[PDB]
Amino acid sequence: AVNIVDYSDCFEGISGGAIFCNTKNKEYNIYNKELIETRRSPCSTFKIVSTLIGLEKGVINSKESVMGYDGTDYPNKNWNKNLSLEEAFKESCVWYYKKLINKVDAKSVQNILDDLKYGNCDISEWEGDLKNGKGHLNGFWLESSLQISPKEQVQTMAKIFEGDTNFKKEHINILRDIMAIDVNDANINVYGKTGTGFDEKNKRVDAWFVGMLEREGDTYYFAIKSDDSNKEITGPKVKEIAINIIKKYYS
């Protein structure tokens, strides 16, 4: 079932959409249906799935796991260390996740994405958007071949966290741990991942916050997405919007 809602009062004039799905019923609450059905690059929200792939394949094993930092200099101080999975996820550290995924064969990734119904499941540009000049800081999930709609993101999150995929429960629990966020409200549990990209062809941001809300035995899977022309709109900004929606409409 689809219920059209209006969350514009939480978007602060930023263009976008939101979708929330409750496990109990079959209700999707949808703000901006056209946008919620449009596939876009997941950007760093793909780290939700790449973490699970790495765990399943044994590239990493726990929230402490490391990827063998080699000393390469980066502008973000927190990337210049042998950071753990938990830290790499929270920092959105591209080198860690590029190295992780490059230890996994493409057929294994293809089959996992197919089974998750992860959007277009298109990994045909493995090295990513090389025209941007960033070299190895690139991949199929970053403004490249792989695209997924906000609705598909919510459907994928629900399958993962309701225990309906092939991934091990222990691995799902690691993801829950590293996705947990502080929202200054002890009576809900919010989990998610930001994503920040720019679609150069259409001159619009791909700014995401995707995750899950737990409130008194109810669970909602959500995806908030901006497509604003304002290049200053980032994943963290959309996360603020998501929290305002949760506080106003999901309390």
Image (tube, helix red, strand yellow):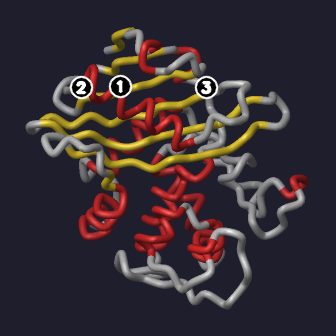
| Residue appearing at x 54%, y 59% in the figure | 111
Marks 2 and 1, how far apart in space?
7 Å
Q: Nearer the viewer, residue 158 or 189?
A: 189
* Amino acid type of the residue tagged 1 in the rendering: Ile
Element under disc 1: helix
Q: Nearer the viewer, residue 132 or 146?
A: 132
- What residue does disc 2 label? 250
First in sequence: mark 2 vs mark 1: 1
Residue 105: tell me if it is visible: no
Marks 3 and 1, how far apart in space?
21 Å
* Residue 205 found in image quarter: top right
Q: Is residue 240 placed above or below 77 in the rendered structure?
A: above
* Amino acid type of the residue tagged 3 in the rendering: Thr
Residue 69: tell me if it is visible: yes
Residue depth check, mark 3 versus mark 1: number of the one nearer the observer: 1
Q: Is residue 123 placed above or below 86 in the rendered structure?
A: above
Q: Are marks 2 and 1 in contact (CB under 8 Å)?
A: yes
Which residue reaches farthest left? Answer: 216
Could you classify mark 1 by the number of other residues whose Cα lies within 10 Å: few (under 14), some (14-19), or many (20 or more)? some
- What residue does disc 3 label? 38
| Residue appearing at x 43%, y 13% in the figure | 9
Element under disc 2: loop
* Amino acid type of the residue tagged 2 in the rendering: Tyr
| Residue appearing at x 33%, y 45% in the figure | 159
Q: Nearer the viewer, residue 42 or 198?
A: 198
- What residue does disc 1 label? 245
The quadrant of the image that shows the C terminus is: top left
Element under disc 3: loop
Q: Position of residue 201 (x, y in %)?
A: 85, 33
